[PDB]
Amino acid sequence: PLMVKVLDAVRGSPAINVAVHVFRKAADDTWEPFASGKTSESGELHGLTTEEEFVEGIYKVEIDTKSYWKALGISPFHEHAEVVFTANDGPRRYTIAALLSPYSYSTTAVVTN
Amino acid sequence: PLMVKVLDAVRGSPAINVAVHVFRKAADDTWEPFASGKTSESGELHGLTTEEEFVEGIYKVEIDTKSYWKALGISPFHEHAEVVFTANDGPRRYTIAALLSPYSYSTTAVVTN
Amino acid sequence: CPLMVKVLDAVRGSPAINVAVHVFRKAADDTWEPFASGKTSESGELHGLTTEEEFVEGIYKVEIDTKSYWKALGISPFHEHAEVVFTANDSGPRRYTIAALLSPYSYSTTAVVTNP
Amino acid sequence: CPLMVKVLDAVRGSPAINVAVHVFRKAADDTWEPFASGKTSESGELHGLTTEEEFVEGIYKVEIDTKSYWKALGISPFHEHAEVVFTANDSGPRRYTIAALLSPYSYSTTAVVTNP
Ligand SMILES: Nc1ncc(-c2cccc3cccnc23)cn1
Ligand SMILES: Nc1ncc(-c2cccc3cccnc23)cn1
Ligand SMILES: [Ca+2]
Ligand SMILES: [Ca+2]
């Protein structure tokens, strides 16, 4: 139900081995750890969660862009990229995609049935 | 060796049934038709060309964004999106990805071995 | 003006007007503290957030209220906000312009950093 | 200033300076004719391309020479250029700002259209 895909605009490649943490907003307005992983050779992170676990609510996907750029020897601006959205329930799969540059990022959601 | 992927930033979906034409630059600096198709339900267009046909040179990928937006009832700015690049030969596959909004588009290249 | 925020609307091809922007700074106890806030003008720009005196080193978060923007236009957006988190002034004072480009299911942001 | 072009560099977090920009207009015989050209300033902006008199209805192409920009910085880019093609002034005169954000393997562009 939730996949994350990361691309690198400088190298023209998938962004490989990028740490990604997902949080869900708790009733006290704090962020509870929900799922995490590292992107694969294709820049994709699958298997984050299951249908039963992914309930409606506010999620944060935190992509560690700074570590990624430093591992490539490139100087970065942002601490990370945080993408915060509401999951709303018919049948739906979410893909959070991000395109990374050192001083800019773009993110889009691909929500399909 | 060449794939095109198109996303819609307004609807949060793949951009389905988008016409795409690819041209290769001829010796007289004109644009020769090379391949074309329409994006699938996943927003992807595969099978454009073969290894033997896709030689080094300057290519143009013309995405008919205006037709796409009009078919969705949304008012567009651009006539189309044209993405022009040089193909250079080790082992390489090219993905041209585009993210569409009515008054903006973004494109990236994903070049892998 | 060491910190300026500019917001554009990719649907309409226009400045994003009356967009709320909240800026936070990480405190020594590792929580986010309020730093400054404002709203974009008719040009989509937000000037006057801070001053050279107030804008010290730190980790800053600029939270752009994209959800309210789209909801006011009658549209149901995907994101809650667009957030930009960065370390500022580590090698001395700089001027930062944070720009954001908004669509209902996407946003982009960029930083332009100049040396006064 | 009915037509302005702004270019930013996503690698350095800076204006893209000294970027060549060529503008063409489709002729009645369906070919591209030269219309105007210039280069971005130290702010990454290009003003003075055209005038209200000259900038009539038509289909325009704005070709930003991104390849030369990156090659001058010692970088081998992917794209030949970034091109923006649009119909202008169809419902009367408008002011257009074409902005582009550049990386070596990517670019984005947006249009801001205002009614004088
Ligand atoms: N699989 C896939 N997903 C998205 C893109 C993508 C393309 C262009 C711009 C972007 C801006 C933000 C996020 N993603 C994109 C390319 N390939
Ligand atoms: N003055 C100005 N205009 C536009 C942007 C801008 C911001 C974010 C993404 C972009 C994508 C393509 C083009 N421009 C942008 C930033 N400053
Ligand atoms: Ca310091
Ligand atoms: Ca007309």
Image: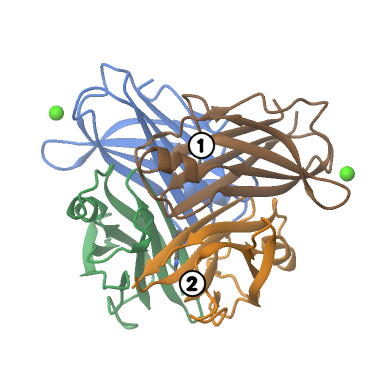
Chain colours: A orange, B green, C brown, D blue
Disc 2 or disc 1, which is closer to the eye?
1
Q: How many labels does the image show?
A: 2
Do we see residue D67 in this rendering? Answer: no
Is the CB of the residue bearing disc 1 within 8 angstroms of ligand 2? no
Left or right relative to C61: residue D100: left
Q: Viewer-proximal residue, A91 or C98?
A: A91
Residue A88 or B51: which is nearer the viewer?
A88
Label 2 Cα neighbours within 10 Å, binned few <14 / some 14-19 / many ≥20: some
Residue type at mark 1 is Val
Residue C93 falls left or right of residue A61: right
**Side of A48 where D56 appears, left or right:** left
**Image quarter in which the N terminus of chain D is found:** top left
Which amino acid type is marked by label 2?
Val
Q: Is residue D37 above or below residue B102?
A: above
Q: Where is residue B45 in the image (x, y as percent from the top left)?
A: 29, 73
Disc 2: which residue: B111
The chain ID associated with circle 1 is C
Q: Nearer the viewer, residue B73 or B47?
A: B73
Q: Which residue is pictured at 38% across the width and 25% down the height?
A: D49
